Image (cartoon, rainbow, N blue to C red):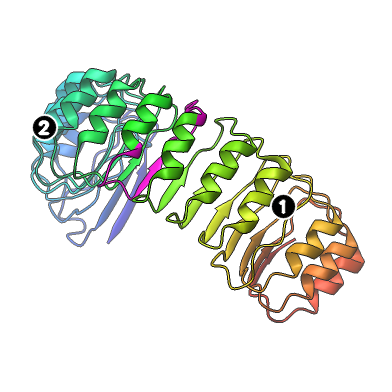
Amino acid sequence: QQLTITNRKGSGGIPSPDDYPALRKLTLVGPFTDADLQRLPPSLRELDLSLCEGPITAVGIAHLLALPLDRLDVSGCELNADSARLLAGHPTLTTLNLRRNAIGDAGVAAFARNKKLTTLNVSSNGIGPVGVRALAANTTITTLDISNNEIGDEGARALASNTALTRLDASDCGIGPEGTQALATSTTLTSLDLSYNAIEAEGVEALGRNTTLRTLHACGNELGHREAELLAANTTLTVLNLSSNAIGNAGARAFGANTTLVELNLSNNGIERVPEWADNGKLTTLDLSNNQIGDTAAQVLAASHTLTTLNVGSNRIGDTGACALAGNTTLTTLNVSLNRIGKAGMLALATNTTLEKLER
């Protein structure tokens, strides 16, 4: 019902459908040729050609069209816009990945016509803003990744005009404040990832004033505590992630008041003090890894009535904090990796029965 073939000596003959007619997944690894997948069993409903390194050309894709699978490679194999058009051709494919394939603008333009693809990943294919203007025409992909393609603010606006996309990853797309507000004004987007982007304070303010997003990523855009306050004010988001910023103690303190967020990842923000999240808040999943949390902040954290999933790896909590945390009977997933905790704290944690998963 599932296979993984990993030939590295030239190209291994594919097993005919006679060998096994009961197959859902095929994973292929190493160098291969196009006829190899020509012999593919129609039993197959999925196909991973990420790990293959062979010189697959448009002819491969062509033979694949026959297969009734609804899943495609996770990396492509230096496909060109030719295999992009060809792939939009595929009838049953509901999820296709094409990351790091460098099909031009033209290539992605093709999927503008697809009517079955619900989820497309065309990540770091060199797509300028014009393939975006093209592809935003689609009316069917509900989920789409344009990361590491330089789509400026115009590709941002283009996408903000689309009205089928509910999930858009746009990390490191060269977006700025303007395209950020463009996207902030959408009303199909429930979840959006503008990381490594250099959106500015104005873009953050746009997003703070949004009321249609439910999930938002802003990792590595240098957001300070101002941005943190702006965001924290937003009462509509349930899942926020601001890793690798400088939201400092002040931004943490801001989020302390937010009784609306459910999960909040504040890793790598140089936080030292943590505030007191409101009781009867909604936050249940806090991530504070790679901060500069001492034992004191661990005791504060340990006092939360609502947290059930705390991550506090790569910090400085010693035994006192490990104990205090262990006293928490409401937590159920606690990670305390890479800390300063010693055999006393290890024991103290061992006593805790309420906990379900623990990394130490």
Between residue 162 and residue 16, name the one nearer to us: 162
Q: Going by the image, does 353 lie left or right of 223?
A: right
The quadrant of the picture occupied by the N terminus is: bottom left
Q: What's the amino acid at mark 2? A: Ala
* Residue 143 visible somewhere in the drawing: yes
**Magenta region's main secondary structure?**
loop
Pointer 2 residue:
62
Stretch of the chain drawn in magenta: 184-201
Q: Which mark is residue 313?
A: 1
Question: Is residue 187 magenta-colored?
Answer: yes
Q: Position of residue 245 (x, y in %)?
A: 62, 35
Q: Going by the image, does 309 lie left or right of 140?
A: right
Q: Is residue 148 above or below residue 231?
A: above
User: Given the current orientation, which residue lies at the most extreme bottom position?
Assistant: 353
Q: Which mark is residue 105?
A: none
The quadrant of the picture occupied by the C terminus is: bottom right
Work out how far the residue at label 2 is from the one at label 1, CA to CA, in angstroms.
48 Å
Query: Which of the 4 image quarters holds residue 98?
Result: top left
Q: Position of residue 339 (x, y in %)?
A: 81, 52
Q: Residues within 10 Å of mark 2 (few under 14, many from 20)?
A: some
Q: What's the amino acid at mark 1? A: Gly
Q: Residue at x 52, y 30 (%)?
A: 201
Q: Position of residue 314 (x, y in %)?
A: 75, 47
Between residue 227 and residue 300, name the one nearer to us: 227
Q: Residue at x 70, y 44 (%)?
A: 250
* Residue 9 visible somewhere in the drawing: no
